[PDB]
Length: 119
Length: 228
Length: 210
Image 1: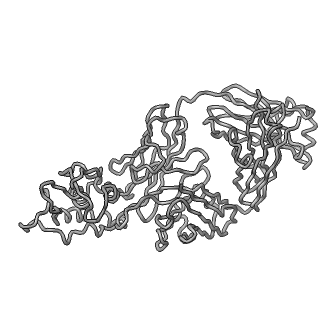
Image 2 (image 1 turned 135 degrees about the vertical axis):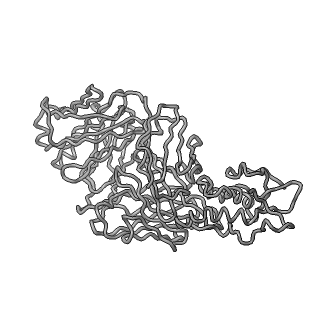
Image 3 (image 1 turned 180 degrees about the vertical axis):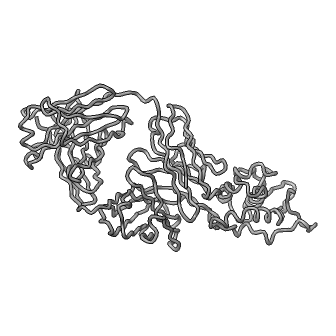
């Protein structure tokens, strides 16, 4: 159940395999990619180096072939991508999407529950 | 096959009113945003009016705000644009422009322009409109060069622009060229349209040019008969 | 607030690159579109969402993004690619278009103009008017000046000339008119339309008696 990642913006993110449907019930990687595409200027602007990993960890979640419980990113990955960029959308009449919320994300502190995070 | 047809373009007196209507087809009309983009003759594209899928959040450009109103009616797949207090700086070709793919179920998405109409010319002048006088450009041996006869009809003394012509109700298109219109010293326009055709078909084929002058709701079908 | 180069010149088969960017206040995370306007035609979108081609656009048109600058890339430029290319961007509050870029394809062949001169039609004469019609076609480059002659004497008043425009050939056509009274049309022995192109003149002559 691990298809190779085909979404262009999600190349070089640390992992190369994903599963569908994702949390947003996208049927194919074409459906999700058209929603991640909207962020590629935000990535190119580089308002947050964690924005790259955060989106892909949500739209193209990691598909470990050994391990079959969903691995989400930590809330810290979201809070850095948020506050690092969120002012940019806020200045120009856009808004941090409700899909990219950080509140209910698994914290890095909890030792039971995993969540991906680099630095 | 996406089609966007704009009607209601013609002459509008300064300080007058304007209503344009864009008829959409080939796609789910209610599933895309919708915009009005204009282009003054020889100038660049200018942003005018934009509207969402349902019509709750109209958006307008600078040289238009407070004077225009964009709206849609998704029952008959029609977009509209109304304008008041038109000045000379409003003469332009007005384009109907469809939105591109948008990711559903998210509040973060950007608009694009996917399809363009053919546009309708809105001339802001105080002069009255004037239908055209159409005269034949009759083929002869004097207009035949090496077995190909050149023929046409002259569309003289009309206002405002544009004038479109076709030939044999659009069945003859090879060799047709309609020239730009010249503004004569009278303030009226004139143009010509020529088609080049084999010599023998002067007798075996009759040639009608279909002049259409929408601003004065006029339509002339002139038989171009040769004479020697 | 979108800027793009006014003109780009390329040879047939080469690759053209047109750049579009936003000014010091434009939405740096917004997308760029590209629309092509061939002479006298309605615009047609080549690129939306920075690097996406709508259905029907050939794949030699491509878009690329670098910071706040998008580049339209046209490979295998043919003479038909001669057009104006506008870029556009939207920050959800408004739209902004660029001034436009004119693509000229260098090295198109020279062509001497063909001239057709039409006398005033019988119907026009019976309406008490007279118009001479000089149609100039199948020439390149699109630059031409016209002179009229009553008999052999030049006539400057009453002439109107059209700026050359592309025909379906991707060659150029042009037109010129001489308005006269019916009395003037019958009073002379011949009228001439003198089209000069690239130093050389093509001239047609019509006679009322003919």
